[PDB]
Image 1 (tube, rainbow over the protein chains, first blue to last red):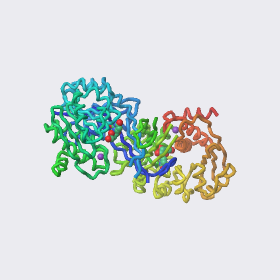
Image 2: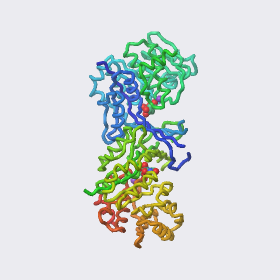
Image 3: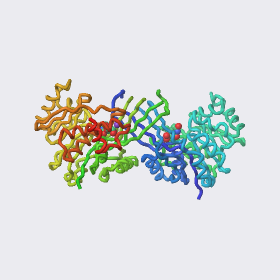
Image 4: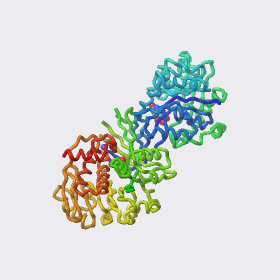
Length: 302
Length: 302
Ligand SMILES: O=c1ccn([C@@H]2O[C@H](CO)[C@@H](O)[C@H]2O)c(=O)[nH]1
Ligand SMILES: O=c1ccn([C@@H]2O[C@H](CO)[C@@H](O)[C@H]2O)c(=O)[nH]1
Ligand SMILES: [K+]
Ligand SMILES: [K+]
């Protein structure tokens, strides 16, 4: 009865492209994918074999319930997700071409994931092996999670350069943070011009009380640092990338899962990279052939 | 046990706008509305009080099942709508601004609404008081409907200038056609420069065997013509137009419904205009306050 709790946003990604110029109902292709950092992480966790509870918010509309249902049949326990009356399920609209042209995000239902709401599941949350939170939620909600985790490790996904900042004053309450270059720069106030500067950035994070840093630098690789002194680089699992979406979602899932499985820091980072790689090689936001098995086959094939 | 059968397309309309410039996830607002000419006509018919069966196609995805469910709880009988495996539910994506910027339509599952499919409901179709078909379906499918209607009146919505053409050779099999200016011009090969040319256009339609013509000219009004000699104009119900979508859908519903209610042609046209007016004054694709009562109140306020 070990379970993982993911507190994040549940979205519908809608992607459309043509086969193009404006003020015209132009023929093309549209796809509805299930999305949202929290939701995607929960799903990757279920595909990794953990029993994952999603604490998110969808609307009273029917498409919310289709998001929930689709998520549930992926192995995720969505029966505490909040259904909000009157308001609409959040979404990520994305206009492409044969390659993004533009994108809209409507994610205000994330503000419904309140302190009140999580407080009604305090005990349940405090009896998880691991809590994973994304920064789509309000500052009040993230503060509540970090203040009432009862020594349950909180893994935090910073999401964006804009949304990561709510983490700055609470690095001492976070077990593992996984920022990208821009996010780390935005948090520390130190430029990540090159591979020379990861040390000062990590040192900044550790002096502000961050237990573990998992820093994705892109092509440079992943730099990981433990406040107890262990640090290192891991070079990318070089891959045939079709779409990049769900990469970080998969990596977060890998980190939390490996932690729950008793794996060491470095090897958990390598495994997580394998996961994100599987994500990079799938047209969909989450890969339904993500497994401990073929992630390990992607890793031993190093 | 009188029922109405609607054979058309079932879509999800997605509308997104900002608070906008490119290569950026712009915070904004997204709405999923149920749509598709056929589906909307069925819904307006249910709100007009008829018991309406929808023969459409949605995908094996979950959002299809949500389209069906929302439509069913709007009062429509969707239990013969086809759920197609492997392929995804069709949709009308719309990028707006505070004013449409661009639109994509993905409507290829409409080609799954086959002759085989309708033939498996031959009996049921042939025992309706009226059949309503849209030109989103294939030429083979429309030809099958018109060839096996068993003297059940077929009301046809032409949909677009591009899609209306499949109606040209089968006007003698159609009870009532409702084209716009552009559609009538495209069908007849006669220019509708002004209100002078409605007579020649209508005469062209009647010599090609069309029983009834309901011609919407926009601000000019609605010109209606019976192959038996009755014709006339009806001036628009001037309204507070918020968005225009679902106008013609509402009008078609009004026409079919009024026909089923034994109403005369002209008064059915006036009533139908009232319906479209209710639609014009609702932000949504279908107005849930469309009713015999308050449309008739929109008409008596003439
Ligand atoms: O602020 C944002 C932007 C995107 N996403 C989600 O992240 C995924 C892309 O990695 C998609 O599911 C998208 O909905 C969020 O959760 N928050
Ligand atoms: O070829 C098309 C284009 C649009 N629509 C639908 O018609 C409505 C607008 O009148 C919307 O629901 C839209 O999805 C169709 O059914 N077919
Ligand atoms: K992916
Ligand atoms: K409308």
